[PDB]
Structure formats: C-alpha cells, structure tokens
Length: 152
Length: 138
Ligand code: NA
Image (cartoon, rainbow over all chains, first blue to last red; front, side):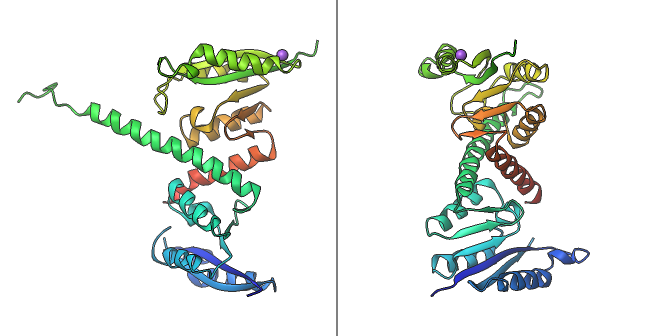
C-alpha cells in the first residue's frame, strides 16, 4: 500500500434546481478535494439518489474488503437514515480502523470526539427505542374493545 | 456575600421497591454526598419526577419546576444521570440545554460525562442537531 485510501459517500438530489447536490457536481467536488492531498488516493465515489440503499451497501462491502481507510460524507443525516443505523455502520467501520469524516459536523469518528459521538448516539438510541415501546403500549390502550361507544 | 455555586440535581425516581437504588431517598443521599465533597457548592434543590425504570414513562412537574427555578436565577448548574433520563426526546434535549446555556447554566450529564458549557457540550449540541436533521430528511 502506502497512501490512505479515501472514499466519499453522497446523497444525490432529485432535482435539478439544486445543482450543488447533483451527482456530477459531487463527483467533481470530491475528486478534486481528495486530489489536494498527495498522501491520499481516491478509492471511489459512492452515491444513492434521495444508508440509503445500494451504493451505500457497495461501499460497506468495499470497507469489509479493505479498500477504504476513510470515508467522507457531508452530514450524519446523509450517512444513515436513523440513529440505530448511524451507530451500526460507524461502529462496523471503527472496529476495522476505518474512519468516517462528517464534513458539516467536523467529526472524524476515530478521535475522542468520535468516541463522544458514539456515546451520545447510544443514549439517544436507547431513549428512541423506549419511546417507541411506550407509544406502542399507549396505542394498544387507545383501541376500544369493550363496546365503549359501539355495542357488539 | 458571593454565594456558593448553587447545584440542582434532576432525577427520575422509582417507587419500586425492586429498585431502591433509584428511590428518592437514595438519590438525595447520593447528591448530598457529592455536594459535601465540595465546600464551594451548595444544594439548590433535588428535582425528582416519578418514572418507570428502563422506560420513558415519567412525570414532568419537577422538570418544569427546575426549569422555572433556572430561569428565575436560583441555579448555577444541574447534575443529571443521563441524556435518556433528562428531557424526553432529542428536540426537547436541544430546547432545554440551549435555554440553560443562554443563561450560562451548565448541565452535567453524568453517564456521558458531558458538561454543556464546555467544548464537549458544543459537540453534544451539534450531534443532537444532526439527529434531529436526520429525522427531517429521512
Ligand atoms: Na458543600
């Protein structure tokens, strides 16, 4: 090897009046940005229109195969669909010493700030799961099966 | 006549029984001992809402009382066990942390080891903002 293998993960906008989030604009942005650093080599640019589906999954498989050392992505909200998936995929990369760099938030997931990200997400996810569970139990009680308003 | 640092504790308490370490009186003892270790600190109050352990089923009257006391200038900092045992969701965590921060009132989340007035607190606010944005976008 030698060079750090750098990928980018992109969410592509469904229009058009948003050229900045177009596929082509993002391909050029990341290709040029990663070329700024001669210690790095571009692995690939991965993009789905919209964790997120097919190219995200291709990226994860390339990570499991040792093709990528660091993934750029614009934001947590583009990286994955929810807290639980953000945890899952950040941790899966981290166990293999693969960093994600969240550009908007300015967080490399392998730093102590990365560790705090994961602590905060774990607490957030526990609360979200308990909230769903509470809401499900409340919802069951709302259903009228005693002939409250209408007889049998 | 400069007053000691006025420390509140926010707690979700259990009436079970099978969980007496989460009782009101166990919590009073815990925070009494902590504040005793620091001669420059004084208890503002214990703020405690009854809640079912391992759940988000919780009262909110004391949380509201605490927020009012913070806005009324009675409290310099708030200890609380966890993000998941404080406000009820992400948007509310953001709302209340920001409101306290605007008044320079620190919350210390004990399990996460996050003081909301430090750089870690700035990180907490960005990560929570991202979680909220992530919901909106997905
Ligand atoms: Na004291």
